[PDB]
Image (spheres, coloured by chain):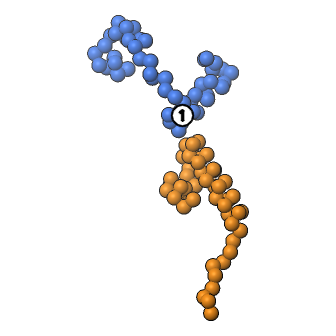
Chain colours: A blue, B orange
Amino acid sequence: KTRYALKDTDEEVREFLQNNLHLQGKVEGSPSLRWQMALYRGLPGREED
Amino acid sequence: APARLSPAIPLEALRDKALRMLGEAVRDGGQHARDPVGGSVEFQFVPV
């Protein structure tokens, strides 16, 4: 969203779709990030490994 | 009179309680709970 706001189009998004890799931070980095990971992992209706 | 002596308490039981208290405190700190024992990190860590 901020890239789109900073004068970018769909071509730039496609080119930079795999540029970022460090965004997948550890689950212990925040006191509430464990809850989000737990709900995203351990639910029958939400399975994404 | 040779003054008096300080009152005595069970040293081993107090030491065991202090050890388990510090263990619980460090476990809570590792778990990163939002509710401190004394309402702040100071009142949880400094006295023990």
The percent position of residue A26, horizontal first and vertical second, equals 52, 28
Side of A44 where A15 appears, left or right: left
Side of B22 where A1 appears, left or right: left
The answer to whether residue A48 is above or below residue A30 is above
Tell me if residue B46 can be seen. Answer: yes
Q: Quadrant of residue A27?
A: top right
Q: Nearer the viewer, residue B15 or A12?
A: B15
Q: Nearer the viewer, residue B34 or B25?
A: B25
Report the residue marked by disc 1. A28
Residue under the image location 34 percent in, 17 percent down: A4
The percent position of residue A33, horizontal first and vertical second, equals 53, 33
Q: Nearer the viewer, residue B22 or A11?
A: B22
Give the secondary structure at mark 1.
loop
Name the residue at the bottom extreme.
B1
Q: Tell which subunit mark 1 falls on.
A: A
Q: Quadrant of residue A22?
A: top left
